[PDB]
Amino acid sequence: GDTKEQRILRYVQQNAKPGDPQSVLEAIDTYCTQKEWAMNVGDAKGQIMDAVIREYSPSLVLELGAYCGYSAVRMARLLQPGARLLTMEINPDCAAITQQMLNFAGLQDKVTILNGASQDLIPQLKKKYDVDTLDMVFLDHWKDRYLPDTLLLEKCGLLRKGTVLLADNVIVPGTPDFLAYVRGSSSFECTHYSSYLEYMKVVDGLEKAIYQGPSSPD
Ligand SMILES: [K+]
């Protein structure tokens, strides 16, 4: 069998318009809706992502996780000239499709795909990828890494006061430990957004968690 991601790219290349990111997003959602691939229909969560990008105008965004490139296209299309999206993905085959998707959208120059495990790459951002602090982090990778990677970003000095974390799929299948941490911590100011999943007909959600600076040494 062909993978979902390679079939999504096939559909985009044959139906979307090159250099037209909206047409790419719509083609992905159209195809995934037809196939009833609920986790790959991104328009509902995309509305929330777009509003965050529009409000905060981040210059440097870290994306954790990529499958077919939908979220990278969604974010990169709203980033300013000169901005940078760093996208970490452990599966090289997903990284490959994501790269091809960005090329078709004409957005490749704004994005750097890093193929590897987030916990290995995060400690390299400062010295190897010339990062000071991140303006935004989009969490959409392995569920059990949301909390550990947040703690790792903190420890590596990659978050500043005002850094916006936006976490996807916090309800389904869920990231309850991550939610409990950010909601209970004085280092984060949190907002929850409902986001519907078709077929399962359930309200998933995203969490926006804005870093406030580290806890007191007292
Ligand atoms: K809090």
Image (spheres, helix red, strand yellow):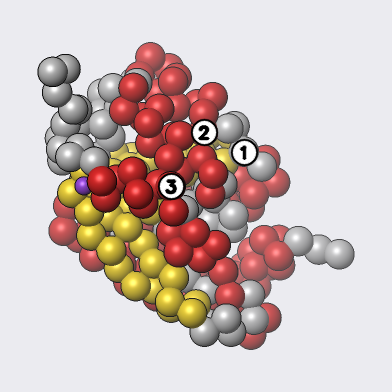
Q: Are marks 1 and 2 in contact (CB under 8 Å)?
A: yes
Circle 3 SS class: helix
Could you tell me how far apart the alpha carbons at marks 1 and 2 are, in whole angstroms?
A: 7 Å
At x 34% / y 72%, what residue is drawn? 194
Residue found at the far right of this picture: 1
Q: Are marks 3 and 2 in contact (CB under 8 Å)?
A: no
At x 44% / y 27%, what residue is drawn? 122
**Mark 1 surroundings: few (<14), some (14-19) or many (≥20) residues within 10 A:** some
Disc 1 or 2, which lies upstream in sequence?
Answer: 1
Disc 1 or 3, which lies upstream in sequence?
Answer: 1
At x 55% / y 62%, what residue is drawn? 173
- Image quadrant in which you'd find residue 74: bottom left
* Residue situated in front as seen by the camera: 23 or 180: 180
* Residue situated in front as seen by the camera: 49 or 154: 154
Q: What residue type is disc 1 on?
A: Ile
Which of the labelled discs sits on residue 177, or is there none?
3
Residue denoted by label 1: 90
Q: Position of residue 216 (x, y in %)?
A: 14, 23
Residue denoted by label 2: 118
Left or right placement of residue 149 versus residue 69 in this view: left
Residue 43, placed above or below residue 51: below
Q: Position of residue 77 (x, y in %)?
A: 35, 58
